[PDB]
Structure formats: C-alpha cells, structure tokens
Amino acid sequence: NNTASWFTALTQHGKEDLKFPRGQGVPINTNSSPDDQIGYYRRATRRIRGGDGKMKDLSPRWYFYYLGTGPEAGLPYGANKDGIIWVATEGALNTPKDHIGTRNPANNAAIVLQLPQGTTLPKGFYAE
C-alpha cells in the first residue's frame, strides 16, 4: 500500500499488449540520469458492474516502473510474465533503481507521462 508508479498511465483500447521498439518506451523524467532509463510497464485490468448487473471489462491501463522497483521489483530485465513488458533506453545500466523507488500518492502527485520525440506508440494506446 501507499506505493504507485511515478507516472500516469497508458490506456489500451485494442487487443494487442503494449509493445515498444528497442530503445524506446521509457517516460521522460528530468530528475533521473541516463543510467536509470530502464524499467517495465505493468498492465492493470479494471472491471466494473455494468447496467445488466454483470461485470464488464474496462480498458486496461499500463503503468511504468523503473527496473528493480514496483509490484515486480524482484523481476530481472527481460523476464517473461503476462502483463509485463520491458523497455530501456540504449546505454541504461541493468541495475535496480532503488534510489528512485516508487511514489507515495499521499506525498507526491504522479508525473504526467510523456515520451521523447519520435517514439512509436502502438495502435490503440493513449496516454491519460
């Protein structure tokens, strides 16, 4: 509890999971260094009860966590797991970013997720 991504989410509207080209995907954060630009996105599925009384699936959201932090802090870069996709800027160090850690929403608002110029966002995905 009291732990969250440092950034706002990407919303999925299509059917394909989130995917980034090699070297792309890490959100902008001017308080981090080139060594830190590596991590993963984690899918969060939302389900609400619709008008018919049955549960309906909402659009999935994907949250970025620096490598070695977040709900899959123990996962090494590249580990295969459903809902987890890995991203890294070229040159980033394959080390845990415990100095960055996660965000306490009671203490800090989320950084608005932004991707650098030229990034290919897959079809159906949009930043909140």
Image (tube, rainbow, N blue to C red):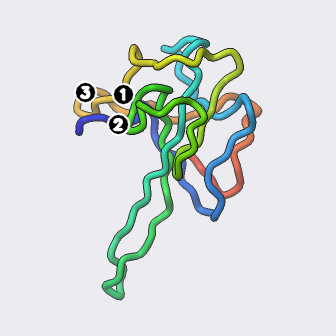
Disc marking residue 102: 1
Circles 1 and 2 in contact, beta carbons < 8 Å: yes
Q: Secondary structure at mark 3?
A: loop
Foreground tag (1 vs 3): 1
- Measure the C-alpha gap from mark 1 to mark 2: 6 Å
Q: From the viewer's perspective, is 59 left or right of 25? A: left
Nearer to the camera, 76 or 115? 76
| Circle 3: residue type | Asn
Q: Secondary structure at mark 2?
A: loop
Place of residue 87 in the rendered image (x, y in percent of width and height, measured from the top left) = 62, 33
- Measure the C-alpha gap from mark 1 to mark 3: 11 Å
Foreground tag (3 vs 2): 2
Q: Residues within 10 Å of mark 2 (few under 14, many from 20)?
A: many
Q: Circle 2 sits on which residue?
A: 4
Q: From the viewer's perspective, is 110 left or right of 15? A: left
Q: Circle 3 sits on which residue?
A: 107
Q: Is any part of residue 128 visible from this angle?
A: no
- Tell me the quarter of the image containing the N terminus: top left
Place of residue 100 in the rendered image (x, y in percent of width and height, measured from the top left) = 41, 18
Is residue 54 positioned above or below 32 on the image? below
Q: Residues within 10 Å of mark 1 (few under 14, many from 20)?
A: some
The tag earlier along the polypeptide, 3 or 2, is: 2
Q: Quadrant of residue 116?
A: top right
The tag earlier along the polypeptide, 1 or 3, is: 1
| Circle 2: residue type | Ala
- Measure the C-alpha gap from mark 3 to mark 2: 11 Å
| Circle 1: residue type | Thr
Place of residue 73 in the rendered image (x, y in percent of width and height, measured from the top left) = 41, 31
Question: Residue at left 38%, top 38%?
Answer: 71
